[PDB]
Every structure is written in structure tokens, then in C-alpha cells.
Amino acid sequence: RDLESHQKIQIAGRYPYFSPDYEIKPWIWYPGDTVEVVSGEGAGQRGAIIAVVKYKNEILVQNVNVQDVVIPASETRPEQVVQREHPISVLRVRHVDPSTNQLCHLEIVKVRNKETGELEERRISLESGALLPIPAPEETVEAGDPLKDTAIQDADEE
Amino acid sequence: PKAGCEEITRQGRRVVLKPQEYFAQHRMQVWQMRFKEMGPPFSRVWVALGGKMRRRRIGRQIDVKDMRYYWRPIEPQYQRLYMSRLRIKDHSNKRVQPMRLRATNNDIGQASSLKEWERSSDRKYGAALAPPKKRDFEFRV
Amino acid sequence: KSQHKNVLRKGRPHMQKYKELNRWQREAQGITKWEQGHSHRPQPYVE
Amino acid sequence: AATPGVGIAPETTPVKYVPEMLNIQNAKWWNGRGKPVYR
Amino acid sequence: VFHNAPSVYPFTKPFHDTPYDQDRGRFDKTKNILRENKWPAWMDHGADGTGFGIGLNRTHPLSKLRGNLRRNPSEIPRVLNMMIQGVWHKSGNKLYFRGGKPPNPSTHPYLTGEPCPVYGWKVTDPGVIREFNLPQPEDKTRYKPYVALQ
Amino acid sequence: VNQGINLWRSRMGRLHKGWTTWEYNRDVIPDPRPFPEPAVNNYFGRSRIWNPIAGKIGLVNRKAEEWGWPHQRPPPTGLRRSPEYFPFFFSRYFPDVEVRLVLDSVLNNETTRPIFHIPQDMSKQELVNYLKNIYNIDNVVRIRVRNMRGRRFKNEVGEIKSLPDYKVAVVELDSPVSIVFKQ
Amino acid sequence: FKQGQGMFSHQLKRILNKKSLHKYNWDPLHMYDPRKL
Amino acid sequence: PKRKKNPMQLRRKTYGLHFKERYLKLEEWYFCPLCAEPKKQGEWCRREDCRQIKP
Amino acid sequence: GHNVIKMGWMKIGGSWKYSRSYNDARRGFAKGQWQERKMTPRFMLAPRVSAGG
RNA sequence: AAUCAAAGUUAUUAUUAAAUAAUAUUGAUUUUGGAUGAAUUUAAUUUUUAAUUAUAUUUUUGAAUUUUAAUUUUAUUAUUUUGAUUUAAUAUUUUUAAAAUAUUAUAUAUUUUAGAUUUAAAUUUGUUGUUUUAUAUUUAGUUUAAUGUUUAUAAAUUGAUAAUUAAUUUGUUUUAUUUUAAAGUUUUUAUGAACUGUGAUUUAUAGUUUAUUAUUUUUAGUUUAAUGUUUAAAUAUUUAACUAGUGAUGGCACAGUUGUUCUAUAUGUACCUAUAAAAAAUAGUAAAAUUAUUUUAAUUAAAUUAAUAAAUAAUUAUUAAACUAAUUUUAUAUUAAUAUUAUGAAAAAUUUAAAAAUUAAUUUUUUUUUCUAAUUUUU
RNA sequence: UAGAUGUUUAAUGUUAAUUAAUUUAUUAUUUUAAUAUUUAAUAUUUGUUUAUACAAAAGUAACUUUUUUUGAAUAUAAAGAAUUAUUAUUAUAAAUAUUAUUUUAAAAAUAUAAAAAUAUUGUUAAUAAAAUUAUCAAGUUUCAAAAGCGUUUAUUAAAUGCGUCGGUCUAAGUAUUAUAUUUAAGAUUAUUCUUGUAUAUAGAUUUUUAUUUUAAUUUUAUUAGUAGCAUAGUAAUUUAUUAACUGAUUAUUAAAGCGUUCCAUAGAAAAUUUUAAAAUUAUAACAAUCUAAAUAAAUAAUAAAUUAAAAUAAAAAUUUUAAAAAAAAAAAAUUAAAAUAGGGCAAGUCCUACUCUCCUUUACAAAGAGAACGUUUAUAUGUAAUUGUAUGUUUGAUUGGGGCAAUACUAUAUCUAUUUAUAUAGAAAAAGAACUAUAUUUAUUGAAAUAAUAAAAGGUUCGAGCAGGUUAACAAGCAUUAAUACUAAAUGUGUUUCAUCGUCUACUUAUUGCUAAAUUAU
Ligand SMILES: [Mg+2]
Ligand SMILES: [Zn+2]
């Protein structure tokens, strides 16, 4: 059967990112970019974005909302209490121009690239036209299973 | 969720506009034949004929076999009873007069004198009370 | 009789008979209850 | 066990008593299963 | 609507009461005649006294064998009475369903063949018994489950 | 209807006093007081029953993946009755089975009766064929097969998330097998 | 003393609402076989 | 009961020496020299010292 | 207010000891029923004249 | 001993409801058939999932009613892409949960004791608080339009033709509403023969009296009695009686103006008034109710009639009226128009009647601003 | 003070153009629905000790890994009374398991009775069919009334059942047969006479009685008869008993038994006689099990109480009030200790019944088809027909318009008589006219208890009435009101009544009530 009403919507309250399109319109915030919190807590705290979890529109803004972490450890290693910057929302964070250093609105544009024709969706400020590209992710260096991988030259044999 | 929280989620019959009555219903015909209402404004007798004028005549008094012939008023205690069914047309409107017994000539057209009937050529200016319509000599059903 | 011991019931209970199944076969078919069109008669047995 | 409620008519006149004979209202929206067949 | 019969008012109304009569409907009771059933006899009453063959025998499309797992509206009333009631054979042992977790006729392995008295089953069709026949690559060109990276 | 002659007319030889079928005349169907519950099997006990009644959609959802249904015309019924029909061809050559082995009976304790789990629709003689031709197992004299209601539980949210059901098949190998675990 | 209040009477009142498949099987012309014409 | 009782009816309950003596009486006690636990007189422990010489 | 007959105009929430016939003149006049319960209605006493009226 | 008047704040969590909108619609919640089909069939000239701009006619005299509106022309069966719009509604759960004044031989809370008492509503048909409802808290709880500003105009009459010196208003057409709760019923079709009827269904698991296979009977579940009396039970405990069924708790079979009946108007799923379903039946004709303090003109009546009270007078009421001799320089509620579910008058004065009261009678028929003053005294 | 001679809301309350103290004043004495109390210091609850079968329905709150077979497949512990409750679910089979849920220091009642002298029915409507017992658990007899042995929702001269008999049936069942009934077997007998249904019938009705149905009012012969027998009654006699409203006998005009009567008659219900354990009167006589407290925490009911007592008057009522004047646990006198039955009236509906009311009606008859059979008509209207009426007022009669009775009139008391019967269809077509209705005049028959009912009030049993006991004082059919029958048992009470001074009889018949009459004397 279904739940008790405020626990019915507690199920909506606890996991609000399960509704589709809870992820915002084409992504604008990536790791490391210039950012500061304007609303909520500590207005005017300039930080770099450490890590981003997308599906829920959440970001680890460094040096802001650093929440004391209760790290759980085994008998092997002794636990520690070190604080980490807690996943903080983005609806209350904006961008400061890496050059101008003032609160800028960062939005997408399509730009014909130079020597390549991707027309990749490029972020641009609405005041400075700061052409900020989308950062390219990294292929993990130490990835790969040694004993259970068919080699590409051995797996692409047409 | 509020009115009954389960009686209003599962659905029963929904009610709609309720049709009206024949809004000259209360000029019933046991007056449109028995009486006739005479009089100037603000005094309308309902004059009615004699009581004993068809049943037993032989032997009744000589000068009372004729009191049955005059258009006597009906006593006002009944005027107000019968004319009560006619007042109800728009109550609480202290300045509309009661419906009349017979249909006065100007109100019959008052129905078709309305801004919505101006496009019904038939049934306008009196077509019911008109003489019977004349048709093509070939008219046939 | 003023005493219904109600223990003479309860012995050799009847099958469950799940009458919702025949109630369903009616709707899962065009026919209503087979109104006295048949209504029935006891059919013979092989014995 | 069942009942037609109409009562089996003579084998010669197979239909007496249509439900319309009684001024019955059987709109599909009123009692549901209504709409007759002789129609 | 009792009179959906061939209209014959002064003559005798053939069959009138019999098994095969008209004016009784189509999806009626009184159709014991129609005992002809595609499912083999032995799977609706066991091949022997112990009700051996009894059950619901799903079958593979290709297999010519016929099983009694029907889903026609006329046949589900008995296919549930197998899954929830089960059969109490007249020999004393309860058949196809005897305990708690009611079987899933549609997740049975397919009927492979009619039972025989001498052995158990004449395996009438083996084309229903899958024999996974993938060659084991021990000769050359080794293939791990998933591929390498750039 | 309520008053007047139409009230008394019931005495004046009128059985059926009609209900006012001009008032509710908003024509949208009510629903009966013995209201039906939806077709979803609410139960998640061990006596959960398979619904035999065939649903319309389940056929349509079958076609659209068998052959592009609204767009690609059907394969001729001869091919569909043939072992060369793709889902009969994707099966005869690319089986899809999950014969998972339970280790709690084949761990450090030696066993002659290692237990498996096989999909509910793998009969005995197929489990033989399977281990024989895929895992080289060549010594299986008797297999012993149950059927278990898939595990059930309540997730932290609260919906009863019952896993699929399976089929314990305690095979009985000749020479016992074992697994070592060095700590 | 009715019987069977249990779960099978709790499914068989919920799963049987499932609408069976419908195919307009139109009447078979038994006596007038059309293909033998 | 053909009437509900106001508190002044429920309160008369607490005046007789039946309520008082049943609920509202403190028990006379003292410290068992052997067990150091509070104790009434005439009652002892399940213990050799407490059982041979009544503390 | 409730213009109860035979008793002025009463307030709402007032006393309904005397509205025995206001609760009975709110239902409305009998519909389809002779207004005159006894005494041979004055219409029936007078004679039909001029068959149409 | 006895009283003693007494605590208004949880704390903490977020995108449903309802109407509306005139674009889709072969039956929502696994994978027909899986023999090869015969088994997955709902269709017919009637107010129908089709929903219609008048007051005149005409009519069993009395619940019956008005005809294309522009001929495919738009009144038409409806949502995603503004948390889809709008306006009305607003929560539901988790855990919150508090408090210090009046005697000392007794009527009822005021500090200064004494004075003080219908609890209300109805019902009172003045058989005049007439034996009815209410434990308390909070929430929810009942629909007659209090208004007429310039285009603009109405108004009668015969039975009928007609006649209209016959004298005269108003109105840019005013309509819609009509209490609330409550039956037994009543009709319209769907479900039920697991209880119980009857149909059918079992061909020999204990005792015994008698010559007898018939027949007395062991007889622990059942014609009685106690207990129980919201009980361990919406029928159980103990117990009396009875008990001999080759003819019967039982395959499936009969269903509601009807089945069944060794017939009792009995039963056909724990009140047979079947259940289930769909209505707005009636209930003003002594049922229960009908929500807003501080106001600003009074009263009773009692007759014609009733296959016995919805109707009439008279009263009351809402709205409105004009100053005819009589007097003082007194004093005067008279009316019109509508609204109106009523038959019976304390103490007298008398009058019918075995009244043993009823009946006639006809004058009564109480709503206190506060401080104060006063002429009628349980001598 | 304060407009005035008493019943139709006051609102720019964030300027519904709001923006940090709006301090919102507006809240229905009952209704349901949700909570909370009272009953409740409680009613229930309470876990100390152990006599074995296996099926199927039924469940699935359900854990899992465990070694089923040599079958493919398939599935093996758990119900129903709302519950973990009264509760062996008896499909089978078996017979020695040291299988294992029951608080506790008392006497009242009460459920209950071990034990125990007399007495034996005097108790009571009535003793005797009334648990178990190792003290081994059983009354005998007579008479009168009474059939079959099956079967029943208030459990039986209920209804079955065999035979006989009446009727029907030779193109679906065997006419010593099977339908359709009435009776009841067995044994005696089964009487007199017909006005209607039925049959037969002849265009039909109308007529019309071989047998059958129903009838016999003085049928009344046989036969039993104060009897389940309309009153009269306790029938009058006889017994029987101390006492005979018992019961049995004789006969015998029995309010109107009667031939399907009567006899015969067995376990039944009575009446004797008699015996007898239930603790039957006398009669009272705890051995047993059923604490408090500690714990868990329900129910009816609930306007309030500081009054409640008590006495007295009352006035409409039973008294309850008003007034005066006082002054913890058992029991059931009062509050409503009760439920719910018992009335009767009103409007409403229900259900059944028949010479008179009326349809849907399937039968009978006519006609039409060269009548090949189905339909349609016409005339008919059936209780087979399920519609509606069957009153109102005073109590059972009356219904009209007058008059006399103080220009009062309940029907009071008396009488009169062209005092007139309005409308609508028909009838009379000029001005003139007929018919009929509770005579103000709306409807289309008359009857029932149907276990009648639902929504209401209101009485049979009374602070006041009425008619039939030696004539007259008295049982007691209408003005109130959950008081919810008479009597008995038990248990009280205030009176009042001659000289101390006064009020305890027990029985028989019937349980009606109160007498009769037996015990000396009552
Ligand atoms: Mg409220
Ligand atoms: Zn100690």
C-alpha cells in the first residue's frame, strides 16, 4: 500500500531528484570554475568547484560549507574527523568572471571552432563574452583489468 | 481530500442545469374559460358567471333564476388565492406586476421582441395567432 | 428447539469453489449470466 | 441457476414485453448496462 | 432470449432438450459434449492410478506436442483451479499443487513428451530439450569477456 | 415528477415511476459501489500467483521488438514457424541463462552435492546439457530440483521489492568438488 | 464459517480485472463454404 | 452511573483512610548492615549472613 | 431576517417557536394541487362559458 | 475531618486537491493462439453516453406544451513544452501534552459575610418546566435577489363577429428561487445452492434384549433444565430426552411474483423486509433541527365548511393610506394592498350534562438600563 | 443615564491600490466525526508441572542451503468462528513417551454442593425423564384420554406415510396402471336432504343436481357426550380426599359434537395407591473451587450539582418539584436497576382474501384465411388478477334546512319539510330544460391482524368516570404516562378499629384469587 502522507511526500522530500528533468537545463557548472555563494550561507565566499554530482544539481564548493565529516573506519585504520566541503546547491551559486572578477551570468553558445568544425556548445558570459569552453574529461590512467580484457588489436580483428 | 477524501475521488453522477417550466404555467385553463379578469389598473375583478345556471330550473324562484346571469365578481378572498399563482413570476421584485390571466396583445410579442429573436422571421410578429399558414398548392406530406 | 449446538457443522468442509472465476468468465465473454436461455437440467453421468 | 426476468414467451411469438413497453429509461450513462438491442 | 433456435412453431423443434440443441447459447454449461479437448487425455487425468501425467504442460511453439496451458477465456477458470486448488486425486495423494507456493505454469520447462507405462516418458520430441552447443574456444584467438582500452 | 398527479399516478396504475434522467444529464459514467480494484497484483507473499489472462498490450510489446512493428512489415508466417526465426535463432546459438552457483555449499567443506540456481525454465536434462557442454562437467548422475519464491524485502523507501524467482537444482557429482579460501 | 478469506481470494479479486485479449472472430460460414466455389 | 462526576466528587475519593493507607504511606525502613541496602524489618536476604543472624 | 408570517420579521438565530408555518411556506405552494382544500373551489362553482373562454 | 480557586504550546519535515480549457481515444497494469485454428463474435428504423432560443394555441377542464437560423458556420466533449494555465480550497503526519489563593459542627464561587437560584432547548394545542433531547472538546452543519436614471414606445373589450366619443400608469423587458435530517416502502437489472432447502448422491470402523434377517437397545456432540445474559459463543458449557436411517449432512441441479417446502407465511450465506446496485418517493399535516445581543409602536380570533382539515372569515403580519357635526381647547389603530398549514377562552358571573369534566360562555393571558426613594403586615 | 413606544449584522480589520507589532472578537448550548473524560482505587486478564497419530479443504503474517525420487513437470508444516478464543476439522490408521502453560493466606451473595438424625410432598403452577458414585445410580401398580414410529422455526390429534374411495387418463409408459386429490391404518359401522360450483346441455347466458365438489341452520338416526365442544358452571349426581374449582362413573335435550363416527390403545400428559437418593415444607445446617494487594485498563450510562435525606400541604400526574419545616464493601427502595414487551390513536406503506371496483391475461366462444396448425379482430371480462377503495363524526348512530328553548348551542333538548344537491360530457338551440353524487358535491368495490410495519406521540393496570354481586354500598371498557401484567415467595411498613390489650393460623381442589370447608375454636 502507499505511505502516510507526510511520509508519502517524505519519499518525495528525501529523494527529490528522482523526478525527471530535476537536472537543470544544459549544464553550466563544471569542476574548478570560479564560483561564490550569494544566497543562504556566507555571502561573498569565493571558491573553486572541487567536484560536481549532476543528477541532483549539487556541487562541492571548496572552502564553503565544509561539513565536519564523521569518517567510518575499520580496525585496520583509525577513523578521522576531517571536515570536507559538503555538496552544496548550485541555484544559489553564480560565476565570477575569471578576468573581471564580478558576478557574471554564464550561459551557453554555439561557436564555430578553429581548425575543427564541432561548433561545440561553449559557455559565454552575458556581459564580457568570455568564451569559456567546456572542459574535457580525463580517461583514467590506472584503469583496466589485467587478466580479463581482450586486446583491441586482438578484439577488433575484422 | 477535504469534502469527503474518498467520496470525491471515486466519482458518481454530476448534476447539470435544471430545465425550467412553461413560464405561463399558472394561467391554467379552468380560469381561462370560467372567469375573465376585467378592470382598470390596480383593480382587476375576476368576474364569474352564476352558480346554478344549468342544473335545476323548474320550480326555482322566478326572480332568482336570473341572478345566475350576471358577471358577478368573485369575492376578493379568492381573487387573491388564484392571482397568487400568477404573482410568483418574479418575487421580491416589488415593481413587477403580476402575470395577467389572458395574454395581453403586447406581451405575446414581448417574447419575440427580444434581441435574440430578431432573426427568426417565422414565429415573429405573431405567427401562432396568425391565420393558418398557406402553402404551395402542391404541398404534401 | 432452543439449542443449536453448531458443532454438527464444521465437519467435512466444502470445497472453496472460488466463484469469482465464473463471475469473471461472464465478463471475459460477451454473455451475461446465462439467463434462463438454458438455466439448466441435471446432466447424466457415465456410471 | 439463473433468470431472464422476461418470462419465456410462446414459442410462436418469441418476444413479448420489450423493456420499452413499460416506459423504461436505460441510457448507458444512467444505469450502465442499458441500451436495448431492437435498436 | 431463450428462443434463439431455428424458428419452427408448428413442428417439433428438433433437439429441444438434447445435448446438441440450439437455443442454449454458445459459452454455456451443458457442453460436456465438447469433451473433445486438444490436450492429451493423460494430462487431465493421470496416465495411471497415481495420477502421474497430471499437471499443466506448457509447450514450445515448434513442438507439435499439445499442452493444456490454455489462456483462452473459456479455459482460465480451470487453469487457476490447478494453480490454487491443486488436484486431489482419488488415490489419496495431492497432485500438481500440494503445498504453499503455487506453481507458475508459464515458467515451466516445456512438455517434452507423453508418458509411457514401461519407462517414464516417450520423449516424443527432443527439439524442445535445449542442448547448449556453443563451441569452447580452446584452439586459437582468445576472447575475454570485455575489451581493452586505447 | 415529485408532486402533483405524477405523485399519485403511481396508484393510478403506473408501476414504473421513472427517475429524473434529465437532471444528471451530464453524461459521464459513475462507477459501481462494489468498486473494482485495479488489475495490478497487489500481493507480494509467497503465494503470489501468475495471472493467466492474456493482456492485449503484451502482444503488441512483443511485436515491436520481434520486428519493427508499426514500421517494418511482418516476416512471412512460414519463417515465424521456423527455427530460423531470429528469437529461435538467437536462442539456438546464443542462449541466455544464469546458472549461478551457490558457494555456501561448495566452500572449504568438500561436497559431492554442489547446489546451483538455474532459471525456473531449465529442466533437469538441460542442466545436464548445460554443465556438460559449457563447463565441461561430465559426472552428473542425479539432479534434484526445487522451485523457490524469489527473495522479498522492503527497501528503505518502503515498496516490497521482490527479486525474480529461481530454481535450486542440487546436482550430485561423482567425485566431490571443493574451493579453497586462503586467509 | 465461509471459507477461503486468504490471499488467493485477495488476488482472484484483483488480477481477474485484467482485460483478456479480444479478437473479433466473425461467424464461420459452415454450411456455405465459400472457398469451394 | 446516571451522572458524570465533577472533581469534587473524584476528590472525596482521596480523603478516606482507605486511599491514604493504600497509596500515600511511606514505609519504615533502614540500612541492612550486611548488604548496605535499604530494607524493611522482618525481611532478610537469600544469603548466609543475612539468614543466620537476622540483620 | 426571516420574514416569518404572522410574526413580523424575525432575526436569524431567533426563536422558531412561532415559525410553525414559515417552515411550511418555504417549501412552496402545492404544485399540481387544487389551492382550495375544502369549500368547492370558486373556479369549479362558476360555470364553463364559451367553450374556449 | 472539610475546601482550594488553578496554566493558550508542539518543532519539523515539501510542488496534491476541485471547477475550468472544446487537438487523442478500439476495451490500462506482461509476452493470444502456442493442438494449428473452430474454442479470442455484440450487430436489428423507438427522448440514445446524440442533452432542443419563447408566455399563443390546442388539451383526458387541472403538470401537456413554441415550430431552420443562416443550408459543414464557429455550442465545441477538452494538454504538453508559464512547478501548463487560472480561481476556490490546505494541509498530514512524526513528537508534542506543566504549573502555584477562600473552612474548622455542611445549603451552592468572590476575598466583607449575608442576600441570593428553573441548567437549557424544545413541549407549553395554558392535561400551563407535562417526563423529550444534551457527558465534554474542537471541526463540519440548512440559499425566497430589501436598488428600477437621458435614446423608447405598453395600459382595454364581446360569449362571438365586431365595437373602441369610453377616458389611465409603469418597464431599453425585469422571469430562473424555493428550506435541512430522517423511514418502512416502491420500481429498474446485476450477485448467491460453500449456510439451507429439495433433486441427487455411501451398498457392512464398537454394545445388546428376543425364537426372528423384523425387534429391545451401548449411544459423548442435537425436543429438557441449570449456568451464561455485550457471555469463552450475535448460541457456548453442564445435563434430560432421543437415538437402529437399502433409502441420505453430501457428485451437479433448480434464483427472486420466484427456487424449495413431510406446510411453520418456514428457509434460499450469519434478522427473507434476499443480498448488491439506482433513485433526491413521500415525512407539515402534533418527528429532530433551521447559524448573526444591546431592539423602538399595540391586539388575538372562534363564524360559512370539511367521505375532518394545506384552503374562508376573524385575527396576526409585511407595505401604504385619508384628518366629516356631535362637545371638553377631552379622547380616540379606522383602512387599503398583499402575506397567512388554527377550530375551542385562567379566576370569576352562570348554563347545559349520571358527568365523575367536557361544554357553552367572556375580560384576563408578564422582557425590568444602574443607583435611590415607597402607601397592601405568613400579629 | 440615555435617541424614541422591544426580533431584517455592525466591515476601506494592512487603503482585495497592505507591508515590523491588524494585537481580530467571534465563537450553532443538538446533529456526525475525531478526540478526551466519567463508570474506573474495575469488569475481564493472571500460565506451579507431563497419558501421541498420519488425508483434504482452509493459510501463505513464510524464514531458508541442504542432501526426496531414480519419474518431467510439478508443489510439500500454518483454518474457521473479528483473536493465539468454546474448539480433538475423525479422510484415515495406531495402542505403555514419566511429549508438558494456568496467579493467590479469609466470611457475603452466587456458580455450586461433599457431609449428614427425623420427616416424605405440608413445599409448589406442578415432587419423581433429570450429572457423576465401586455404597456399580433402575420406582412398582391401576384407571381415563391418546396415533404411529417418520417429520417440522415458537414442535404438536402440525404436516408425512400403507390401505380403501373419488376423479382423470388407452397416439408416451402398464386403467388390478400411472397421474390429481379427500381422508387416514386396525376393528364396527358409515344415516336424513338439498337452492349453488362442476358435469351433461340444444347459438349463451337463464334454465338443469346418476356419480364427484360443497352444503344440511330441525340434517341428527348410529354412536360417544361438560368433551381441546361458543356461555351456562366447579354441569347434577356417585365415588375419591380430614377438606374434590381435581379425575373417574352412571345417564344424556350437547347454546349449533355427529357418521369419518366409535371402539379398541403403548413408551405422553393427567388422576389415584404406593415407594423413594437428589438439602422438597418443617430446616437452619461453608468440605470443595471462585481475595485483597501489585500489573495491565475495557462497558452500558453521563445536563448539573454539595445537596441529598426525612415530614407536611399542593397542582396539572404517578410523584417530582415549589414552599414550609427540618436537619471503603455489601444489599436493590428511589433516581431510567434496566433492557424491551405491552397497549390503543394518527397519518404512510405493506400483505392476504372473496357475488358485487378494474388492464397488460396466455383460457372459453365468433369471424377471417378452399380453415396447413402459428396471427389478427370482435364479443367477453376470471381474484388464477400482483390496481385502488373498504370514512367522517359523536363511540354502533347520524350527515339536510329551519325553529323553539337567556336573537349562547357540544349534538344539548325537541321537532318539521317541494326549503331545493354547484361544475364538467351527454339531454334541451333563441329569452325556456331534464339527470346524480355522506345535499360544499375533489378518486374508481367491500373485508382481514399480516407475528403487520416504519416515523410519532399518546394508556389497560388512575390525583376523577362506566355496565351485569341478597334491591342499594362493590369487580371495574376515555381526560396522566418506560410507573414496562394478576398470584405466589421473601420482605417491610403508617394507619385505624371494643372491656387489660388486640391483632402469627396451617391446609384440599383451581392457580384463580376469592370464596366455599376440613383441622376442638379459625
Ligand atoms: Mg463551525
Ligand atoms: Zn541482606
Image (tube, coloured by chain):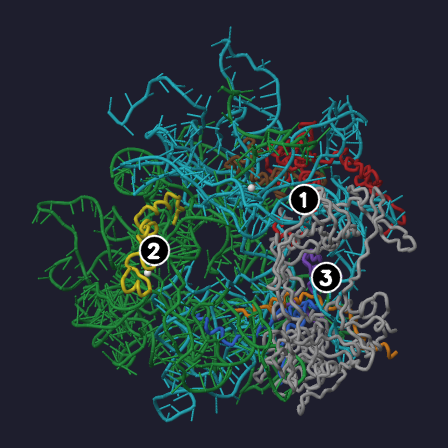
Chain colours: B red, C blue, D purple, G orange, H yellow, I brown, J cyan, K green
Residue assigned mark 2: H38
Quadrant where the image shows the C terminus of chain A: bottom right
- In the figure, residue K497 lies in which quadrant? top left
Q: Amino acid at mark 1?
A: Glu
State if disc 2 and disc 3 touch (CB < 8 Å). Answer: no
Q: Where K1 sits versus K248, above or below?
A: above
Q: Locate residue K223, reporting x and y percent.
A: 34, 76
User: Alpha carbon of mark 1 to alpha carbon of mark 2: how far?
Assistant: 58 Å
Give the numbered dot on residue D36: 3
Quadrant of the frame with the N terminus of chain A: bottom right
Task: Say if A116 sits above or below F50 in the image.
Answer: above
Label 3: how many Cα within 10 Å (few below 14, some 14–19, many 20+): few
**Looking at the image, which is closer to me, B119 or B13?**
B13
Foreground residue among K258 and K490: K490
Q: Residue furthest right?
A: A115
Q: Which mark is residue A41?
A: 1
Residue K313, given in percent of the width and then of the height, sits at 28, 37
Q: Which amino acid lies under the numbered mark 3 shown in the image of this protein? A: Pro
